[PDB]
Amino acid sequence: QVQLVESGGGVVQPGRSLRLSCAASGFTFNNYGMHWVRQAPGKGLEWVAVISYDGSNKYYADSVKGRFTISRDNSKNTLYLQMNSLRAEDTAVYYCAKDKRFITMILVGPFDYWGQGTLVTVSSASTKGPSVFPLAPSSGTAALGCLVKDYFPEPVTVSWNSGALTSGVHTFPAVLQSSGLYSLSSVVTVPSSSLGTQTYICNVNHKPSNTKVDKRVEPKSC
Amino acid sequence: VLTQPASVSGSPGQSITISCTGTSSDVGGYNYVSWHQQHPGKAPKLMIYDVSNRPSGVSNRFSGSKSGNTASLTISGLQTEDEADYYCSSYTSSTTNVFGTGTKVTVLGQPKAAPSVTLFPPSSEELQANKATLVCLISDFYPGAVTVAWKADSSPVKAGVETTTPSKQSNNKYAASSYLSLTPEQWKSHRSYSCQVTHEGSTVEKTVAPTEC
Image (cartoon, rainbow over all chains, first blue to last red; front, side, top):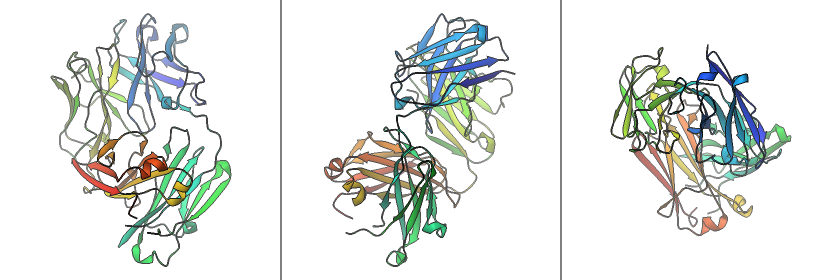
């Protein structure tokens, strides 16, 4: 019956502010402390802040102290996280979590129930097509690729030889850089004997910018 | 500050243990250690609290214990749906709460495979664009959990590293990618760079040099 619903997440520019909320039901909200926990994409859980049942005690992680404030409005069964001076390092899914302990100002845990989270992505970037660079064969089987760099937003899709080449192809998940732009790589393994004869071209589609790029990948000058 | 193994694996039906190593301020100072299970694309769920208690509805094959500054979660009779990320957590002296680094638990469902590593130096076209990315592509490994370390010459490098979390390939083995972003000056100012990938307690290292091809 316990349910927790976060909201208020979205795209925000660095330095700006944003206010997350977490609505609670199925238990006496008035009797329990509440935590905020965040998780950067593909990373570990990071505890953010805690507040006691009546808001008398609040504590913060060092990474957010001074910039984030936690509060609650017991009349609306809602927990809030006020985020200020946002940086790219704050990009994460933000979870609210109920503390197990009944009416106490000690907040030692455990985290009892979790919401499903709200995504906050802090980026100053606008719609931008990608730059594509070759990953040429050098050092039989050979790995070739093209590096799809500095685009926004997701997604980018990649094919090889206009789709004719499928065996051995893997396109990796994107990476989010400091600058707020995405990058990825697509790879394919080839017989080395074909490198001198067969043409290899990766086809990069970025519909959000209405940009298609075909990049020829040739062997390196040594 | 709580240290967990990056990867723990076992065959179906077997018993595994995940260690959580903290300090006299964390795991050693209080009996407030918890364990959380997180399946892909979902929210954590409490498995064990106060070192060794189980919420009702949590299978009794999960068990928690503590000794000194090290807490331990034990999963008996491994089942495929036990495959998830596991995090320990504890109250600290700093009147905060901290999570462990996290452990991917793999229930072995295919043969183990050591990673194949290919390291790409920056392309001439990228350097002419006044950028330099080293691309370390890790493929054909199982279980799908690696840790990547970078070296410039022989000393480690932590600034500018980005690593994807492993996902399955066409051949249903795992692949991951790691990037070292540096300036073209940085690239030429060193003798060699190395990508080291640790997998199942063993490390494979590949090295590129600006003067080779």
